[PDB]
Amino acid sequence: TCPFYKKIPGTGFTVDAFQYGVVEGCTAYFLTHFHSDHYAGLSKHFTFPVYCSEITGNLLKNKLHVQEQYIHPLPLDTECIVNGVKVVLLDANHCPGAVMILFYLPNGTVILHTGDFRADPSMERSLLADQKVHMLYLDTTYCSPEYTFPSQQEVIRFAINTAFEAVTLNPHALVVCGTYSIGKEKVFLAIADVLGSKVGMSQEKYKTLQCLNIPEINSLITTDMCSSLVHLLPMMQINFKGLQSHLKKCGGKYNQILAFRPTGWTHSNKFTRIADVIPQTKGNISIYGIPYSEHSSYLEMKRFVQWLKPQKIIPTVNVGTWKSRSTMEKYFREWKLEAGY
Ligand code: NI
Image 1: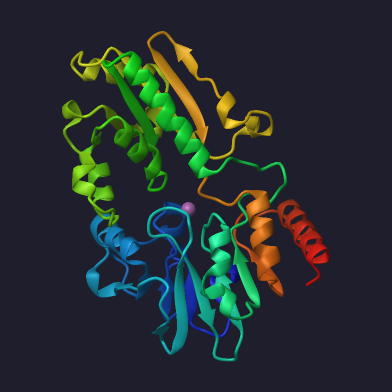
Image 2: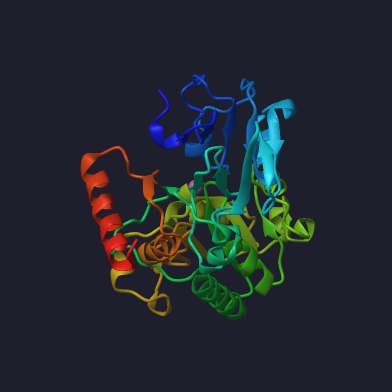
């Protein structure tokens, strides 16, 4: 049965609530983004209205085979009416097609549901600034002070420089990037752009990218592995054994691999700046762990919330345990006392 934190009170709306079968009273199902924990339950068998971004709708039609009649795409930064209620979709700074949803309730309450997001100061100059928001449904993935990470730009600059040096030293080196879902495309697109290459991948991954409305995408990607010096592989294959196996498949055209594993936070964020990163190496294979995050850091989340000044916060991540809920409640109260709301 559907949790309270996926329901928007005083509407017939739900958000990311597809795994409970038919939700009693729901007239419109919103989907924030195309990550499987959020879409769980959606398939060609679904027959109720789904509201989402154009990119999310592309993926629902082509990958999950949801019938077109049930897909209702909405543009971004535009006031729209759904079932007699004013809504706005805003860029979440997460993966492609990911949104936050602003609900203007008939009684005058305003609710922001972040979906998954990486808070940014540019959000403080969006439509959110135009009126008071009363309730916030928050992506609390990294709601603890230990969670720091570098900017996306710092990480990309390190990746571009590392790959350019390795391939300039050895023109027979292949670059590999691991992936398991949409998101983090800039890692492999920026590396391929500095090397003057397309990115090579499986037919199933190419199909996914072709749904993302990336300008000039046909000049950037290919299914011809041979012709390209940056390859994508499942994240599970980015280890010494898998990368050796892959090198054997490529018909000797390469004699070395440099690989990237974009992760979330992992314990060592605590000590190491991006400039100090060194790879794990076994023979002619080197692997770099790079902390490229599409969720808010603690400091990013705290800045956004203290600017928004909500009257109530409803967490959407790490809500299954007491301990976790209690810890998050302590931080929200600190933030409120500090900023005076
Ligand atoms: Ni996500």
